[PDB]
Length: 219
Ligand SMILES: COc1ccc([C@H](C)c2cc(-c3cn(C)nc3C)[nH]n2)cc1
Ligand code: NA
Ligand code: NA
View 1 (cartoon, rainbow, N blue to C red):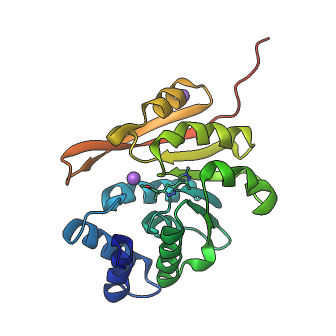
View 2 (cartoon, protein in one colour; view 1 turned 90 degrees about the vertical axis):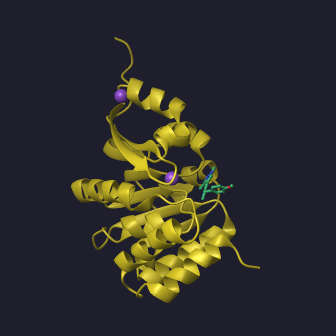
């Protein structure tokens, strides 16, 4: 039967233009703001994402929580030739939607979709997906997983000095354990990007946390 995620994809395929990532973003934002609410980063936070991507021009990006592919389209469209997005999506049907979304956008060659749980896939990146270290991580999956997966990324050797973590929804509904950790730790240099959720009429924010390297042992 029909699902909201199938409806988002159908709306894009009807109204956007194939090979035009920007029209795809605009169709999804129009849909989610005019037709039917959906978990969506939205254009305002999307601008912040764009600016981070443009500032750091990452060659290898890991996304946690693709959902329908909005953020994957958002980020992958700004990646250079040879740059890669790896995106993880725990739900098989959403992973399928994300693939079709990216196919329509013409971005399928820049993205690898991994269908599984973050804590299961993250430790396979080095072996199976030929990853050394990540240049950027976008966290937008389950909120209680931001802190443990960040710790996991670190202990797996996937962060290097200068790796940018960018996490959504750290205020609403909030990830206070993640924030307390990264802001307090000398291993992360943190900044906060406030953005309004107009539909909920509440301020939310993204946290940017730049990995500084592991903590030094006592002398
Ligand atoms: C109501 O159930 C859900 C609510 C939101 C989602 C988002 C789209 C999501 C979360 C993840 C995910 C979770 N882990 C531990 N690792 C990964 C990868 N992938 N995508 C999925 C299910
Ligand atoms: Na989000
Ligand atoms: Na810090």
